[PDB]
Image: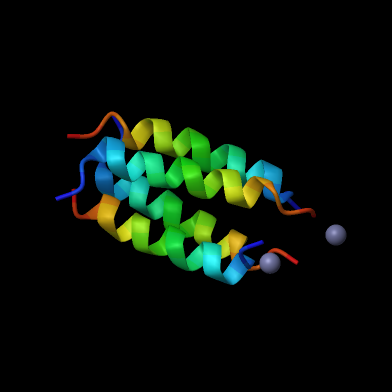
Length: 23
Length: 22
Length: 21
Length: 22
Ligand SMILES: [Zn+2]
Ligand SMILES: [Zn+2]
């Protein structure tokens, strides 16, 4: 199954996408 | 360190806010 | 860019994967 | 309200905590 580091990597990648949005 | 359940809870909370971004 | 709804869906899925650790 | 940048910062902090799980 996916490791904690793998799950955290997807969370960080998702954060990068959220970051791109404007308020 | 923070439990999986505590971290999942905060992530679900965050998802609620992300989904309501305009 | 990905929609807020789409990004929230991915985040919810990851939350449940974290929960099940 | 909190900007997307602010929500993303919180998500990065949560990811660092997830990294410490087993
Ligand atoms: Zn705007
Ligand atoms: Zn788009």
